[PDB]
Image (cartoon, rainbow, N blue to C red; front, side, top):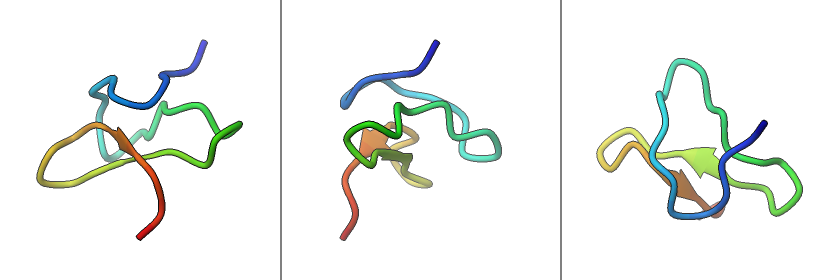
Length: 35
């Protein structure tokens, strides 16, 4: 089970889906795209 873009998750364990290359931000703590 992964988290789509917008879902909030923990930074130590990024649970965002890797299908759209999403990572959990550190200040917002949510799935975001690469900068």
